[PDB]
Amino acid sequence: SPVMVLENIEPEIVYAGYDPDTAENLLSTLNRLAGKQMIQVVKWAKVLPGFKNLPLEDQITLIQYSWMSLLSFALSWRSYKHTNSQFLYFAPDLVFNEEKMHQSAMYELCQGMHQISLQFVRLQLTFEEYTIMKVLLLLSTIPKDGLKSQAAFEEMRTNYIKELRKMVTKSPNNSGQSWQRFYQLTKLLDSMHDLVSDLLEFCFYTFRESHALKVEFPAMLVEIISDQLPKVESGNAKPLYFHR
Amino acid sequence: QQKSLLQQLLTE
Ligand SMILES: C[C@]12C=CC(=O)C=C1CC[C@@H]1[C@@H]2[C@@H](O)C[C@@]2(C)[C@H]1C[C@H]1O[C@@H](C3CCCCC3)O[C@]12C(=O)CO
């Protein structure tokens, strides 16, 4: 059972170190927060059953494709646990929602992330469900022509899907609606591809126009986006769906 | 040009 291991290796909370109250300072602060969070994501994935055994090249590819889904999913969990999904709990010292956003695009991205959090309230998502779904998001995007150890990846992915299904369908808390719930969780994972697509498009823009927009990125994100952007731009990114 | 932060963290 990886569930026991998953609870143990779960990263601890990181602070933003918030302040001038401008769009470029908010974005720069969020990006520097992402860099701190990325260190804890990599240490989490390093000791993850199955993933820990894939070639180094495949581990890098997977993290570079899914870093955004992992961070937005963890943000939705914190938002749910600490504010009942009224606000986006980026860090204990940086908590806000759409109402603080004046630019149309920024409001919609903020709202999209809030809508995932509200779906956690509707589902009353548990920590066990969350940790398995988080792993499934790390395994949600692959290169168009596959990975180095494609079969080993397919085995590990199918195993994590089965762990989610057995956990949901065997729980007495879901009696009479366990399959309906499993399909709601898999639909929520598919809908993560849509949200993440939008968060990545704005991220790629603020990255390319970083100097002009005065939007700062930490070294971790500079290196990740530098490798990810040419892969996404060239169509070398295959999102894996449950219902599509 | 050099080992990435992602690669160093995965191999440390
Ligand atoms: C990963 C990120 C960081 C910490 C965290 O807890 C969660 C996330 C997920 C979303 C991640 C976030 C940050 O980088 C900042 C990102 C990357 C963002 C998606 C992009 O959208 C805008 C948003 C930020 C919220 C209000 C509306 C505008 O900021 C981003 C950007 O392009 C800035 O250059």
Image (spheres, rainbow, N blue to C red):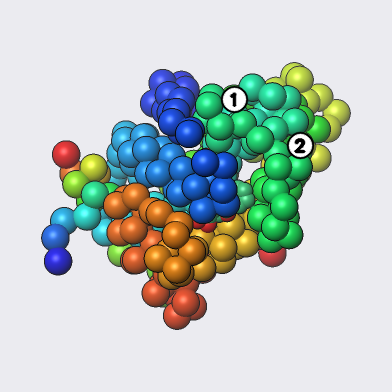
Which numbered disc flags the more N-terminal residue, 2 or 1? 2
Rendered residue at 43%/31% (across/down): A17
Crowd band around label 1 with a 10 angstrom C-alpha radius: few (<14), some (14–19), many (20+): some
Q: Which one is in front, A73 or A189?
A: A73
Q: For numbered disc 2, what is the local secondary structure?
A: helix
Say above or below: A226 vs A157: below
List the single residue furthest toward the front: A20
Q: How many numbered badges does the structure rendering display?
A: 2
Residue at screen point 56% across, 66% down:
A201
Instruction: Rate crowding at label 2 as few (under 14), some (14 to 19) or many (20 or more) other CA atoms within 10 Å.
Output: some
Q: Locate residue A47, reporting x and y percent.
A: 32, 34
Residue A53 visible in the current orientation: yes
Name the residue type under label 2: Leu
Residue A207: quarter of image: bottom left
Q: Nearer the viewer, residue A190 or A225?
A: A225
Q: Are marks 2 and 1 on the same chain?
A: yes
- Picture coordinates of residue A52 (x, y %)? 30, 42
Mark 1 lies on a secondary structure that is helix
Relative image position of residue A20 (x, y in whole percent): 52, 41
Q: Nearer the viewer, mark 2 or mark 1?
A: 2
Residue A126 x, y percent position in the rendering: 65, 25
Q: Residue furthest right?
A: A176
The answer to whether residue A141 is left or right of residue B11 is right
Chain at numbered mark 2: A
Chain bearing tag 1 is A
Q: What residue does disc 2 label?
A: A118
Amino acid type, residue under disc 1 in the picture: Phe
| Residue identified by numbered label 1 | A127
Examine the rendered structure and indicate whether residue A67 appears above or below residue A177: below
Is label 2 in contact with label 1 (beta carbons under 8 Å)? no
